[PDB]
Length: 56
Length: 49
Length: 55
Image 1 (cartoon, each protein chain N blue to C red):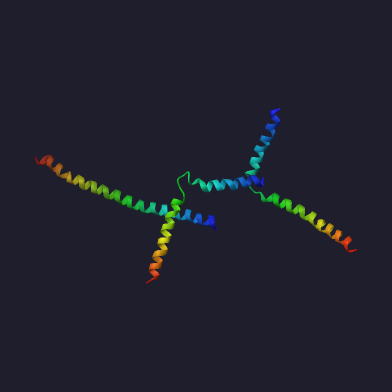
Image 2 (spheres, each protein chain N blue to C red):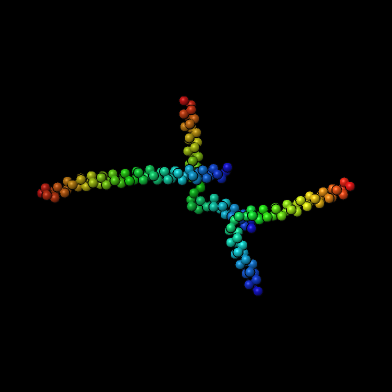
């Protein structure tokens, strides 16, 4: 029973790290695509400069 | 020959320690403890309803 | 010459290959089945000993 329960620690770790990596995949991918849009919002603050380039 | 196979028993004993060279030890399983004691606390708090 | 003491260590290479096979029980069985055939005669010998004791 003693070493077997340490295998249960090990298996509990495998599922924990793998499942957490799956939620990281969602969060990071979502955050990445979102960040491309937020970067385009910074660029849209820069869009005011692109209109300025002929507003003169 | 069987005694050599006991040296394979010593190899597995080495291998269970070996996680410590990879930086795994009780400090990892300690989290499941702090957690599982917390699980008993919340299940006790639930059944106290 | 040193080659004879090397002969022990090259036979130990073979001993490593056969140890790596790791199926030890098979000889454990051999040992205990050989003694069973002796044991039936051995108990018989004890019985003969008792038989002189009884007669």
